Length: 577
Ligand code: NA
Image (cartoon, protein in one colour):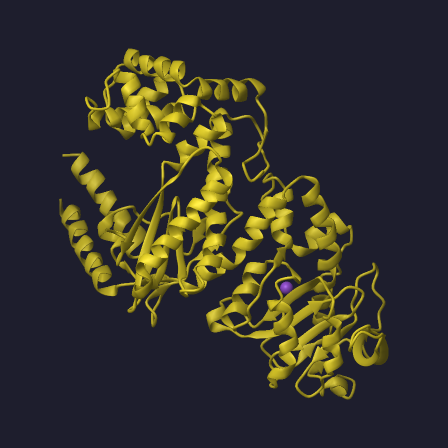
């Protein structure tokens, strides 16, 4: 095979006989400041492509290299970053190729396997590092993980998937592939034909480089149009937050979380013993106890070891920030939000030797947001004077005073608050309290709760009547996250703004946290519900404490402009304390 052996010096296998090595002159304007033209050797296709998408490209080996190529980067503002790797899991794979697409230029492809001189990469590294160069990516979290793990400081990322996923206003589950997005906004059907490629071998296939290169080219025009649609429907803030939240997410996944095997397998054998005890064993006893221990055992304790990286005893879960309807985070394999909320269990999660955990929580942020969005004078003033809404509600229900209040009144107040705020009638309220609070409150009594509640909280009353009357399907957030319902659901309609705003505060907090937590080399570990976990060296204890508090408070203060959030923090050696 002579045609196949045609471009072996460039580590390319010519299968379809469709590749051409062309050496020509390029019109650069760099060097010093004068227009300096330079000759390069690029590759082109014999077969002409249908629509107008760049397919010409350079390949970079340690053998063949031209410093002048770096001059292409000089004075750019955005580029199409797209890498190909030897698999999925970064920790057990290597980066094959790294591609950069530049306006009106053929794609630049670094071959990482054949390269060996570091000097070359300095161009790539400088670009990726350059805070002022926008790197356009498809599924940026993935590539970003690989790069950060392979030590490539990246910054200023624009994610096409995020853009497309937001412009969807969350009304479609599928249709977010590169081909689909391009086919939609650019109106160009990609040739596709991408079979299961093997980047592991040192010979690069012919067609795969073309298609791959195109997958970079389209990111430019696509970035332009998507950018335009974003700034049109006012989603700049959202995009800013999310696209900046990429790196924090990568930090979470890369850092993982260490687990103690002693207490783990101890609890395994113990709960297993109690399980078999219940197996050998009124009604509530056998049923609830057996199935409870069964879930804690099989559905948790037996599941967890699957994701334990044996040698490190770390769990590296995968996070998602747009697969959630509300907008909050979602973790999978395992699902951290699915793990029980007890002390005995979570105790098995520990920091590393010279490190220590810091765990922050947002207190009553749901009702705080609801208070501002609703703009209820009574609730806002109650918060401004540092008073728990449950204490308030309890005082309004029982007509007691703050000294004469008692814990049970706060209990009832909790049921009433979390019940009625999210819109529900006194009947369902009785069921809700009777189920989740075990309170035999008469229907008349719950009616009294309803009337007193809404009679006092006129803000909430107006909010409810507004939503219930307009019966809108479109809904937004303080970050302006638009969502479209299929049908008008009252509860969901009331709930979405709150949950969404909460999510926004969490993400913005993680971004600010990721940027502030660098000096003491502090690590981000976890974000579940309304609590965040960071791991820092025992030296930076009080420091990291102040940092975390200030960061979250700055976020909550960014969105909320007339409510002060209470961030309760605990410096711990365990998740449970
Ligand atoms: Na790709």
